[PDB]
Image (cartoon, coloured by chain):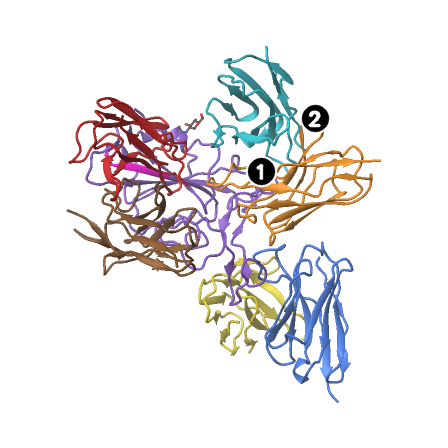
Chain colours: A orange, B brown, C red, D blue, E yellow, F purple, G cyan
């Protein structure tokens, strides 16, 4: 049930960034990961989604198009690939998860979260 | 007046598989709800998985999933426990227990408990 | 696996009433499943003490009493003697057909 | 309407190579996974090759493995079965087949393509 | 790799009959099977999908049934637009083994 | 004291059909008159015991399962049925006793673009023995190739979502099910009607 | 997009009081919202999922309720360890959304 991300740091405005989310302890396939954004000072806000098998990849309206989100069910990781990220998109990026067999976790809720990588623009 | 007896103690190399029997006695076997209890020495008890031999179902615990295949034979009035892929942490005492009043629903207390079967793993 | 939290060791004085809590949750006791109790003498298989949260089988004195209250439970032992240096276990059932046992209690005399 | 045109084929000496291109858009292409089937003239149908949704893993048939290489430029909206080291038995029509669902619990191809043909002689 | 049989291999029927075709497998699939119709000279097309449902674009004179080792495609009423051969197909295990064919002859 | 049926039927979220919850009902009075006069409860089929006569019977205990399925599978929650539910998710025994309540929940358990987390078992090596839940998610070997931990051709993952949209038909909307079960044993009885 | 508003935006209380926190939706949400707790400088974890059930691993002094448009969160007895923000997140559309947060302060 542990969850840990990496791949964050400082970047110029307008480059690409792989963001991992190394999952362990739970069966990774039968859930649907998300990406929750916390700007410094502000509240939580939503960024991306996946599906169970990798079917549809919706986004929030502020970051759609520029974000592409991948999935690797063999290594049980998650990749978020943003392109041409703007200076206002500096935050902490979290990992998530939600499935409804009641055995496992709260339904429709982001039950397990990673430690958080901090992506910050630079100049 | 009802009592259970088990097989003797066994030694196993790390990597083999063990078949532990539980020879019931006293009455009819078809109304039993045998559930296995594992106990490492100096720690608490643990539930393994129940089996209703009038149905053949096997509700395993969430830890012992895919490792143990609990089966039961109606003719010989015994309920096996084919614990495969033995490790060094599985040296323990293994009890079998009838489940009290009901048969079609195993949700009761445990009476009797048989006797100990110290299947140790060493070299 | 073992959802039941139980106190590790409880004690008292010879000739007193000692109690043992058994804190469950909403998925094991609060779902309506009952709670029993077992007694393990050191060097044999454990015994049966309380069934149906209050009763007693033939073979145990009337010093042994237990009860459930909402999510938690209790087991009262009156009159400690030299046949109480043993291990007692709290037993119940999860809602998802899964089995649970208590962590472990150590009753020692003074 | 889903449309599937494919191209290539013709004549080849026994032992040559061809590029069989199944290329038609008709839908959102990069999410699907399409395969290849074949039919000798006057005989039953036969399955030959398939590809994943991203070109990652392929699965060839039993009697065809080792001689072919299926590739797909998913951006180019094209599907290539690259023939190599053919025999007399491989004279058939090669149709393209499109999968029904998006990506998982695979089975049941949806629509069939128009068809190219190949011939062997001397 | 399931060697499908198909019965019959050829038949002659006129308009106003009821023909049932069977496609029986060796390895037990469970409702993973389609049916096909191939006009000579061009490509076949999907007729029914997953052995019960109906594809859009066909009158309901055909019907699929069965689950397990044997399935029955039935035609309730014959028509003069069914002058072709038919194909079953399993897709449970991934080497797809199509059937043989059943020529529907009109007389 | 009255029956605690308010915590079973009126719960805010149910379990999915591959991993369902089972609750025990004990020490109450079985007042079904708070439940039976709810005529949009579109199915009240009772095997073993007859309906409308429940309030004059004494029982030992009541076990109340709970899950959600689509409307084309409610005919499968029954003794002796088949399909992709009664062989891979939840199979009742043949000599089962208990009523199987099943109503419509298209306002409750449904949202736009799918509500992707009500899973159901597609693949298993064998049919389920009765009353056997199954939570294990190891990949199913379809053909003969052991792939050992990575899925692809001939080895799939056995759980798909239901993808419930509110704009489907009457057959694809989520019919939320509660299948109660009753037991009688030679014991004092804690569940009986008034 | 479903705009969700949580009220009030800045609360203050003391130890032991019954604190209420309400949350308003734009259109209907069929009891599919959750309540989060984020201690400052940590990872926000869940307390109440699906507006009425408590996450196993939370002290039972919390309580939330509502169905339809408006939803209330009611803390029964405050503690020194329950002084953090509280997020209102729904689950209905393709675009999931979070609230604005209720800071809890001292007296
Ligand atoms: C569930 O709650 C509704 C509204 O409070 C009520 O009308 C209905 O009777 C309840 N269902 C029961 C008690 O079975």
* Magenta part of the chain: F56-64
Secondary structure, mark 1, is loop
Look at the picture and state if D93 lies above or below G93. below
Report the side of F147 relative to C79 (left or right): right
Q: Mark 2 points at which residue?
A: A42
Q: Does the magenta stretch include residue F12?
A: no
User: What residue is at 30 percent from the left and 32 percent from the top?
Assistant: F26
Q: Mark 1 points at which residue?
A: F111
Specify whether disc 2 shares its chain with disc 1: no
Mark pair 2, 1: CA separation: 29 Å
Residue closer to the observer: F109 or F33: F109
Q: Residues within 10 Å of mark 2 (few under 14, many from 20)?
A: few
Residue extending furthest toward the right: A123
Chain designation of label 1: F
Look at the picture and state if A68 lies above or below E74. above
Chain designation of label 2: A
Locate the C terminus of chain D and report the quarter of the image it occupies.
bottom right
Taking the image in four quarters, ligand 1 sits in the one at top left
Count all numbered tags in the image, as a single digit. 2
Give coordinates of residue G28: x percent, y percent. 59, 29
Residue closer to the observer: B98 or D47: B98
- From where the camera sits, is residue E81 visible? no
Residue closer to the observer: C55 or G72: C55
Q: Is the magenta stretch mostly helix, strand or loop?
A: strand
């Amino acid at each position: 049930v542990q969850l840990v991300e990496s791949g964050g740091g400082v970047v110029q405005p307008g480059r690409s960034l792989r963001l991992s989310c190394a999952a362990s302890g739970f069966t990774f396939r039968t859930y649907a990961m998300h990406w929750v954004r916390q700007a410094p000072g502000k509240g939580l806000e939503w960024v991306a989604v996946m599906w169970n098998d990798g079917s549809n990849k919706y986004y929030a309206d502020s970051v759609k198009g520029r974000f592409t989100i991948s999935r690797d069910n063999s290594k049980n990781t998650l990749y978020l690939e943003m392109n041409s990220l703007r200076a206002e998109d500096t935050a902490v990026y979290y990992c998530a998860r939600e499935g409804v067999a009641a055995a496992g976790s709260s339904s429709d809720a982001f039950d397990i979260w990673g430690q958080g990588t901090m992506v910050t623009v630079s100049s | 007046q009802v009592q259970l007896v088990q097989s003797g103690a066994e030694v196993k190399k790390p990597g083999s598989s063990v078949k532990v029997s539980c020879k019931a006695s006293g009455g009819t076997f078809s109304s039993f709800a045998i559930s296995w209890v594992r106990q490492a020495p100096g720690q608490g008890l643990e539930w393994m998985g129940g089996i209703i031999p009038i149905y053949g179902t096997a509700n395993y615990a969430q830890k012992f999933q895919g490792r143990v295949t609990i089966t039961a034979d109606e003719s010989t009035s015994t309920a096996y426990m084919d614990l495969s892929s033995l490790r060094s942490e599985d040296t323990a005492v293994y009890y079998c227990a009838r489940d009290g009043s009901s048969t079609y629903y195993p949700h009761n207390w445990f009476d009797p408990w048989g006797q100990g079967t110290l299947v140790t793993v060493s070299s | 696996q073992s959802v039941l939290t139980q106190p590790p060791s409880v004690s008292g004085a010879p000739g007193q009433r000692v109690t043992i809590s058994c804190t469950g949750s909403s998925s094991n006791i609060g779902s309506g499943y009952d709670v029993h109790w077992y007694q393990q003498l050191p060097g044999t298989a454990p015994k049966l003490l309380i069934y149906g949260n209050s009763n007693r089988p033939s073979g145990v004195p009337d010093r042994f009493s237990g009860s459930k209250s909402g999510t938690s439970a209790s087991l009262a032992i009156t009159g400690l003697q030299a046949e109480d240096e043993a291990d007692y276990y709290c037993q119940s059932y999860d809602s998802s057909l899964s089995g649970v046992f208590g962590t472990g209690t150590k009753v020692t005399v003074l | 309407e889903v449309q599937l045109v494919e191209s290539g084929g013709g004549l080849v000496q026994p032992g040559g190579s061809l590029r069989l291109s199944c290329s038609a858009s008709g839908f959102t292409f990069s999410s699907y996974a399409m395969h290849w089937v074949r039919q000798a003239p006057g005989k039953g149908l036969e399955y030959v090759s398939s590809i994943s949704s991203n070109g990652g893993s392929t699965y060839y048939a039993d009697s065809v493995k080792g001689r072919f290489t299926i590739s797909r430029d998913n951006s180019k909206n094209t599907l290539y079965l690259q023939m190599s080291s053919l025999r007399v038995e491989d004279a058939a029509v090669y149709y393209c087949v499109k999968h029904y669902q998006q990506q998982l619990l695979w089975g049941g191809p949806d629509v069939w393509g128009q068809g190219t043909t190949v011939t062997v002689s001397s | 790799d399931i060697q499908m049989t198909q019965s019959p291999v050829s038949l002659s029927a006129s308009v106003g009959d009821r023909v049932t075709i069977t496609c029986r497998a060796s390895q037990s699939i469970s409702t993973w099977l389609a049916w096909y119709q191939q006009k000579p000279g061009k490509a076949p097309k999907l007729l029914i999908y997953e052995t019960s449902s109906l594809e859009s674009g066909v009158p309901s004179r055909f019907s699929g049934s069965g689950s397990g080792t044997e399935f029955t495609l039935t035609i309730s009423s014959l028509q003069p637009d069914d002058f072709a051969t038919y194909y079953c197909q399993q897709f449970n295990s991934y080497p797809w083994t199509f059937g043989q064919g059943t020529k529907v002859e009109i007389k | 004291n009255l029956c605690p049926f308010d915590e079973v039927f009126n719960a805010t979220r149910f379990a999915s059909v591959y991993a369902w919850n089972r609750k025990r009902i004990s020490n109450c009075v079985a007042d079904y008159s708070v439940l039976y006069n709810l005529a949009p409860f579109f199915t009240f089929k009772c095997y073993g015991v007859s309906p409308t006569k429940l309030n004059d019977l004494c029982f030992t205990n009541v076990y109340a399962d709970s899950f959600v399925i689509r409307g084309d599978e409610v005919r499968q929650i029954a003794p002796g049925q088949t399909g992709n539910i009664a062989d891979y998710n939840y199979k009742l025994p043949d000599d089962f006793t208990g009523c199987v309540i099943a109503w419509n929940s298209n306002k409750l358990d449904s949202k736009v673009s799918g509500n992707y987390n009500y899973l159901y078992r597609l693949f298993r090596k064998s049919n389920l023995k009765p009353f056997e839940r199954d939570i294990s998610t190891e990949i199913y070997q379809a053909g003969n190739k052991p792939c050992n931990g990575v899925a692809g051709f001939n080895c799939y993952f056995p759980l798909r979502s239901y993808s419930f949209r509110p704009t489907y038909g009457v057959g694809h909307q989520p019919y939320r099910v509660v299948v109660l079960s009753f037991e009688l044993l030679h014991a004092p009885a804690t569940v009986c009607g008034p």
